[PDB]
Length: 60
Length: 50
RNA sequence: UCGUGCCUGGUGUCUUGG
Image 1: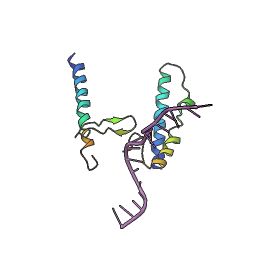
Image 2 (image 1 turned 90 degrees about the horizontal axis):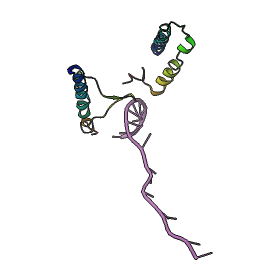
Image 3 (image 1 turned 60 degrees about the vertical axis):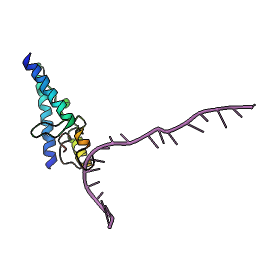
Image 4 (image 1 turned 180 degrees about the horizontal axis):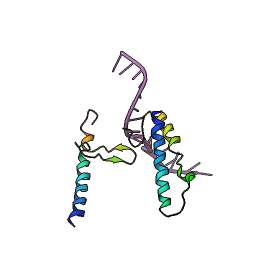
């Protein structure tokens, strides 16, 4: 649960920038490409693998 | 220009200073994009394993 | 009836040994 909080926050940061880059063009934005699958799937799989209870870039 | 040259020599000051010693008080640390701090020359001879 | 030879891994962490 401690993980999944941070990992879900990361993906809301992704869909954010992806909505932005797309509205500014004045076009329309699509969430299917915005949804970065590799946040959960890899974060979990990472922390459960190394043992480091965090993100990979702040793992120290 | 003085401002852009100051940025060049300060960041130059950072890289040259971090080469010998990668443990400064109140200073960012040299790290690889591979997610680890660089072993400076001082780190090759500081510790029990150097 | 033939003639060539030492390649060869670095980094971190947990478990465990006296």
